[PDB]
Image (cartoon, rainbow, N blue to C red; front, side):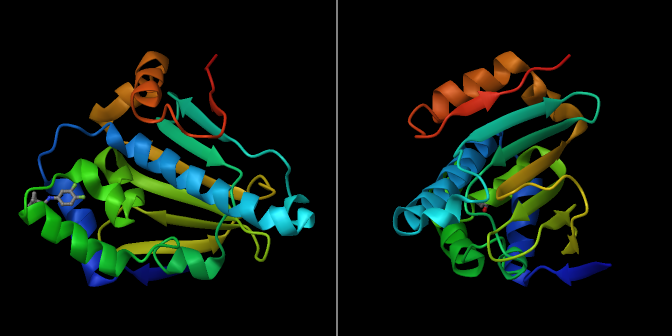
Length: 209
Ligand SMILES: O=C(Nc1ccc(F)c(F)c1)C1CCC1
């Protein structure tokens, strides 16, 4: 059972800008998604400070980067707090409407796309490199769900019957044909060292057969 939703108009406009604007510095998508993972890990860690049982769904707090050249996907996995179904529908737990408003004023007032994270909508920088994004998520207070969008004004949400995740979020980037450099080990390592050197969780870059 798949539910299809329309993006709010401001979010659709944000994704069309990210997709259509000529902007060569696409690598910041990875910094933005890792920083989102770090924020989600901070949240479950804080909650566990007063309720250890919050970590019954997984004690390890980490970030994995999994490239797959056969599928042409880059997956960013974290064991953070995750998202409820309501969170997924409400712009993946962001205040995306007011965030978009600010970001697009900043853009007309000098800023560039790389600053998207300062407006709380860094998730959508995934569409710099991905034609389709799938988000699998599990929050302690809800079931496992899969969100998906190829932009175009709509997204879907369904119960995920795939591999149980325990707790956290998995962002699966179905990369554009000309963006496969972000599956190469040496290019991912470069980006992580350049932009994510101070993330306080272990970031493991998986290698391929
Ligand atoms: O708004 C613009 N681009 C834009 C905005 C948000 C984005 F996430 C993005 F990738 C590109 C134009 C350059 C200023 C006018």
